[PDB]
Image (tube, rainbow, N blue to C red):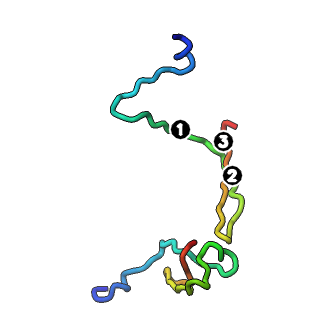
Amino acid sequence: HEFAELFYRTYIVTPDQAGFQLSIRRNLVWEGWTGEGLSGEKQEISKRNILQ
Amino acid sequence: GLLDYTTLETNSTELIPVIQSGENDEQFIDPSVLPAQTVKQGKDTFDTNFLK
C-alpha cells in the first residue's frame, strides 16, 4: 500500500549477490586505556562516540 | 655470511611470549608439566612456554 513502503523504503539489489553489505564509520574521542595487565589480562581503551 | 647463515640472520621484530615469574603465570602452561625453554630474540635471554 502506502503503509508498507512508508516504513520500509524499497531497495532493489542485483540478483547476482545473496544480499547487500553495509559499512559504517565511527568518530570516537580518546581519553586513556584503563589498566596494564602484567598478568596478561586485556586492555580496555575507553572510547566514546563523538555524537554523544 | 657465504658459509654460515647466522651472520646475516637476526630477529629484531619477533613478538615472542616473555615470562615474568610470578605475575602472568596463568597465561602459560603450568611449568610442572613442561620445563621452560630458553629462546633468544636479539640479545636478551628469557624463558618461554606454550599458552593455555
**Residue lying at 64% horizontally and 79% vertically, measured from the top left:** B20
> Residue A13, image x and y in percent?
39, 27
Residue reaching furthest top? A1
In which quarter of the view is residue B48 placed? Answer: bottom right
Residue B50's mark?
none
Q: Residues within 10 Å of mark 2 (few under 14, many from 20)?
A: few
How much space separates mark 1 and mark 2, taking CA atoms?
20 Å
Q: As shown in the figure, which amino acid type bears the numbered disc 3? A: Asn
SS label for mark 2: strand
Kindly identify which residue carries mark 2. Answer: A46
Q: As shown in the figure, which amino acid type bears the numbered disc 2? A: Ser
Kindly identify which residue carries mark 1. Answer: A24
In which quarter of the view is residue A42 placed? Answer: bottom right
SS label for mark 1: loop
Q: As shown in the figure, which amino acid type bears the numbered disc 1? A: Ile
Nearer-N-terminus badge (1/2):
1
Kindly identify which residue carries mark 3. Answer: A49
How much space separates mark 3 and mark 1, taking CA atoms?
13 Å
**Residue lying at 57% horizontally and 19% vertically, measured from the top left:** A7
How much space separates mark 2 and mark 3, taking CA atoms?
10 Å
Relative to A3, is A25 above or below? below
Circle 2 chain = A
Q: Residues within 10 Å of mark 3 (few under 14, many from 20)?
A: few
Circle 1 chain = A
